[PDB]
Image 1 (tube, rainbow, N blue to C red):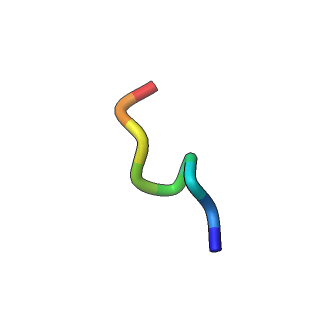
Image 2 (tube, rainbow, N blue to C red):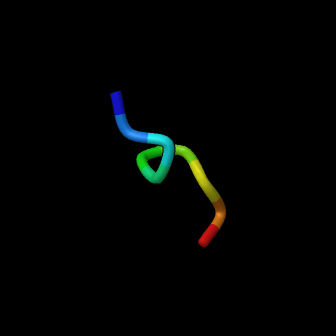
Length: 9
């Protein structure tokens, strides 16, 4: 997965 692939950033 990718906690950043969904994070707002």
